[PDB]
Length: 30
Length: 30
Length: 30
Image (tube, rainbow over all chains, first blue to last red; front, top):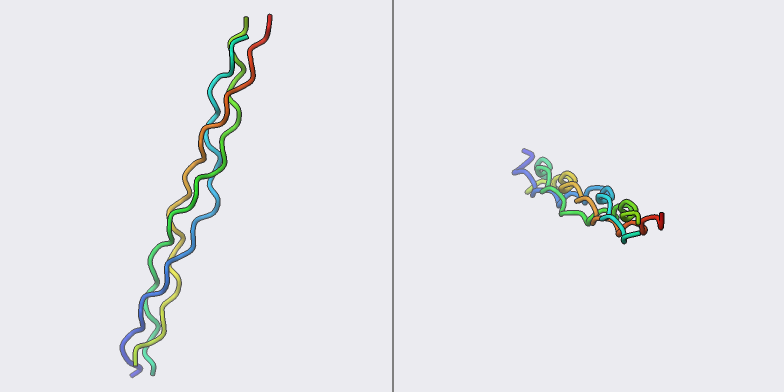
């Protein structure tokens, strides 16, 4: 009364798109 | 009846990597 | 009878930072 609890909910959603990575390496010799 | 709602579900799955970082610094001057 | 499914779980782990950026431009000729 009511009765036994229902099942666990489904998985949450993914987190938002991630931030960009770090600067690239130094370029070619001048 | 039916019983109370089930508990919250599991955390979401992993998300994809963010975008590539910016270009690196200029190369070594001549 | 078993209650209804619970609510969706929380957001998954934060998306990793993206890959390093590309090499920088060439150095100055002088």
